[PDB]
Image 1 (cartoon, chains in turn cyan, green):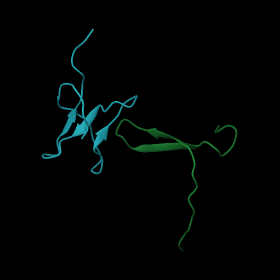
Image 2 (cartoon, chains in turn blue, orange):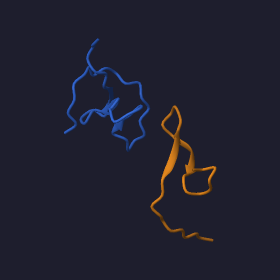
Image 3 (cartoon, chains in turn purple, blue):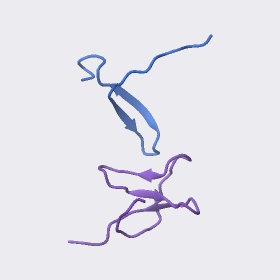
Image 4 (cartoon, helix red, strand yellow):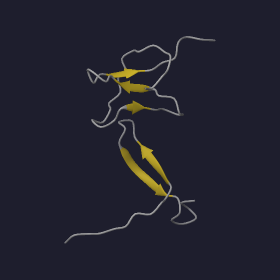
Amino acid sequence: GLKGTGVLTESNKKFLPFQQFGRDIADTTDAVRDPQTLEILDITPCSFG
Amino acid sequence: AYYVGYLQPRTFLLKYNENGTITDAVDCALDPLSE
């Protein structure tokens, strides 16, 4: 249900075993857990300028 | 010995570390230094 647009790179984030989302400075989701493999995936929005 | 506290609606500033662990907190309605 979390909708977004970006590149799904490897996060290198140490989530606690209950945690599902990662936030850094705002309401953006910086890192997200894979629902199937439980791999922690980064959310970086696509390149812009 | 067992301890019973009670919960209040209260604002905190939580110190997350680099590992995602909450290491410290400020009770924002404790004393005016905390405000």
